[PDB]
Image (cartoon, rainbow over all chains, first blue to last red; front, top):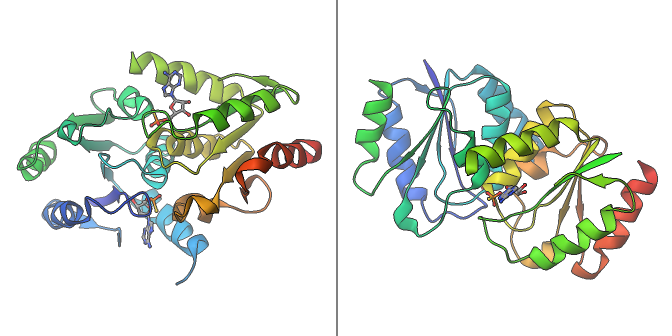
Length: 126
Length: 124
Ligand SMILES: Nc1ncnc2c1ncn2[C@@H]1O[C@H](COP(O)(O)=S)[C@@H](O)[C@H]1O
Ligand SMILES: Nc1ncnc2c1ncn2[C@@H]1O[C@H](COP(O)(O)=S)[C@@H](O)[C@H]1O
């Protein structure tokens, strides 16, 4: 199983430490394809190739980010299963387009609190 | 001719006044098409019908990115507008999608958004 991870970078790196813990936990459920200056053309093409190869896409969507949204858009259009993880304690209301994309199966959006991310991942993969 | 406009809402409404100026100007060039489950389905229907997709990408937003992702996969022509004087660096995925043709990303200053739209649509 191959896993593609999405998380804000230029959108803001507030959750960078959490992302590292998510990527470490994903390694027990599959090969993490992502490597979250060749330039942005190179980054885009490399990532699209990885997204095509992915069996599942996991995104932490608490921090707003164009690139995370874009990856999820390309992923849906490729027919990839998607898990989005969101923390309501951020005080933000999650994107209408991401929340509304949820269908409870091919596209899941799960609210979670600090301390629960590993448990959420276990639940999804097991 | 139909146009779909994308701009941050829950990502932040900092540029909402600018979005209204964009939408006003787009009406010269075509019909501007533009709870959550309903919003998503309605918007995907509009996106599928749109001849061109226009996005102001200065404020980071998951929904705007999502719209652009779905639009690329649908084969729509896309214009993204970005303000470098905002002081942030535009998303690697949006900047990297640029090809100078069916996915264009234009840097502009806040006062010249109308001129940027004029240039694109007079060409298109
Ligand atoms: N340097 C990079 N190397 C690999 N991916 C990058 C890189 N920069 C950005 N990304 C991709 O873009 C997404 C973040 O979008 P952004 O708009 O915040 S730059 C990430 O999920 C990641 O997938
Ligand atoms: N209330 C709404 N009605 C129609 N579209 C909405 C609505 N709220 C958000 N959107 C769509 O989501 C995009 C913004 O994404 P966001 O993640 O900031 S909520 C907009 O370009 C818009 O297209």
